[PDB]
Length: 119
Length: 128
Length: 138
Length: 163
Image 1 (cartoon, each protein chain N blue to C red):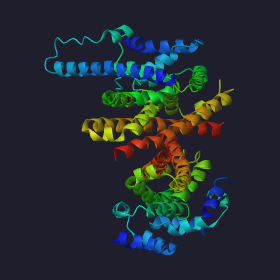
Image 2: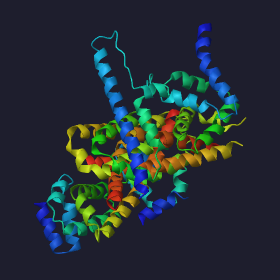
Image 3: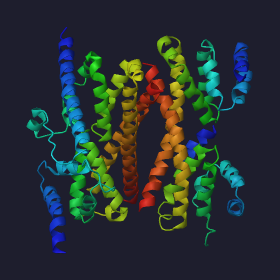
């Protein structure tokens, strides 16, 4: 269903359209979608959800996208490598920037809270 | 951009709307107020269950239970506890308030850190 | 309560003697043995309440001596963790004010802080890697 | 050439250590189940090597022979094992987690294992169960030792601010 639309939106290469249908799908369906998704468009898709992670405040959503992605298409990425090693390398960067920004601040705060909560 | 000014704050009728939030349930107006001014060092550094700190902490707690603005929540919370940590260790109400904040803060931290953790890790593995 | 002095004063006298000793010290080994006791009952800072207790009664110059050795136990990965746990029991049983005061503190405190941060980075990275299990499984 | 002498040596040491340890664990749990029938009269008769060492738990004999191998050879040595040894290893790894015995080491070796034995482990339901055990315990261990240093570093920052 949504899948169909997303494969067409990639089939057209129209970036804005890809984005509309991308944010369109509900978070509960992402599994289903990524599972049935064409492998040839998987590297391209990665480049996308990478660039979305680092240019639009939708953390849980994008991280979920990468999550279900590596989950359903991991062995593939492994064996293939090649050009995908660039795609991979921007995903890593993408989660890294996401990591050290949302972790560094969070736990620090809560640790201080903890000490204060203990006197 | 906004995430450049956010990293700028941590290097360095307002109280009206924030206190009106106590009457209301949505400190939303106040959140926008804060989202405005760049020298929050001047503003943040500023009786009986109607002193500003309890309600500010309550406002960050409110934002946490949303699904947005984790970034500025933490950013504001660290500069809050950068200078107010000696003054709030003296009072009791804002202690129970931080005790409530820590709840939501914890749940969500767990969620997000498992996600960026799982992803960061598995991807670091796959590129090997 | 003379019996109580007798039973409780045992480990107190033991540890205090260890700290007096500027020898390499089985102090490490006493702590080590008592913090990983196969029976952790009851549930508290060291598992043996008695250890928290003797930690609390601590002589202050000896608290300092304990930190001075703690910073040394933080250099090795092996001895590190037990150091982290006694540091933890120490900081949790004592409010900061008693500890801010002295009886040369800051340099030791900074060696401690630095190396603790290092092991923090290390362990975080290890959680990230550890999710490998999560994937492999499912 | 020589690398395989090293590898092989370091393979045999862990393999037989794991044999002794696993047999020991099995005898003691047998004795457990046997004593829960009748608590009176029931001797362990453990292998002489443990009682020779100062009567130590299997876990630590295993852990020590492990901790003893050269960092570099640890890889190929892990790989060279027969698969027959593997489940025991997980059974000990679980234990290393359950008591937080040398976490970074038990990790490093656990990754080396998983990286090379995916399918084999995920096959047999027994190995997956022990793997769920190590998952839980190692996760709990890392959690606790993390939060500890966090609180430690909070208090350190607060006394450094206080000074």
